[PDB]
Length: 265
Length: 265
Ligand SMILES: Nc1ncnc2c1ncn2[C@@H]1O[C@H](CSCC[C@H](N)C(=O)O)[C@@H](O)[C@H]1O
Image 1 (cartoon, protein in one colour):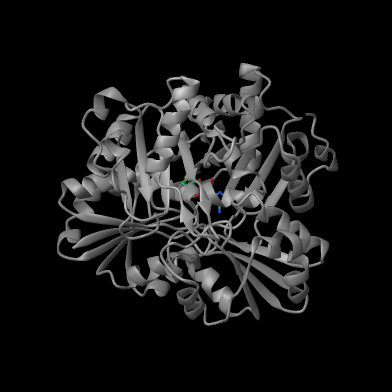
Image 2 (cartoon, rainbow over the protein chains, first blue to last red; image 1 turned 90 degrees about the vertical axis):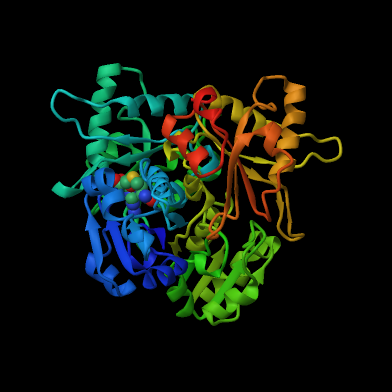
């Protein structure tokens, strides 16, 4: 009678950890959500085949409004698993589900799996230099979110990199590209004119991390805003002042302009 | 003609992803390093048996001085795997290794695995609120490094959490405890007098992340500094001002005192 929060990783169904797979295969009931992130290298079928169980997919409303009604009840008489893309507790509101489990009298365990928060390291940027993170959300109605712009500003001032998650509307199959993210930023730039993100700002694009051949590209906004980075999911990074070694990698591995090798210290 | 950087994960031999394991199996040669960090919950023996191949361990010098002599030569006519604890390239050094592969005309691919950078999410603290990170190193001789203290100040000043890696002497298999780290910080505070770390500061200790039974504890330094958090590895976190839901998780899941629901929110 326990509940397992198990991560499925970034791209493939094989991005789950061995530990996560052994445990999932022995659970009586398996649940999952696929709205917090996009797994572009697999299908629900392959995952089901991998763990050999039928997976009941839950929507954002099932989770946020009825997790303790749909999942926890069974978790008292059986071993239940809740699967999510990437790492199970990286979504802000997921950790709260453990509280719901407790109050319901159900013990829970967490099995980690690859997550962009860690996988960004493939960009070559020093992990310790990453500051506060943010998400670039789609504008809707008269509502135009801009908080993410200030996050970049605050970090850059301290010479820290900014990890930017791009928005996703799973039920509408809408996944923001790095290009769409850049456009929104150029706009907020005109709006706030703080000199944070312009055609000359250097950025890094990471698309489909977790796959064997992710797209890692670095360069100035003017030259990348129009570039094709392949299928989603996309993540966008606005680096702060670079260390020479970071620049070297970005140039040799992400095809960035040779000029960034000249750090203006 | 290919080199695979495969992450082994957090604690034991099952923390590697299924993808990582399968690829390691189909590789002709398998190397590994355990100088950047260790896998406290397993042994080279268990790992070797899981992969079903002999694993040649390389030292820091083997890698830093002769990686292109030991590893790359074989990767030109074979599929080679280089296993590392955690997630590859999160070590500030491994990134350049990809450049070396390129210089030697060897293509490289990265297979991710959970790292503390993402795993800290199990503390219930919002991932986006983590700022700059630091490592707490031991003072020795007439050298007393204290920059990690400064990092905390700057993060908390902006309401951000500080992830703190504790010193490790991999080859001597010695780990700094959270208790030791707390003691060092108080000593530093006693010199800097910045109000950054005191008996009343709220901290979070995460021990044996990746295990099914990790130790997650939150509370004031005065009460945690002599508490036994179990066997290493230990991770210390100094949270900034908390959102109510973060506080509730620390109380419900990490046993923090109710006092935090009014003092640190
Ligand atoms: N392989 C990948 N490449 C680029 N972005 C990714 C990604 N996997 C997830 N993301 C980003 O993460 C966002 C969801 S935020 C939750 C993150 C998730 N648990 C993780 O570990 O990554 C997505 O909208 C997407 O922009």
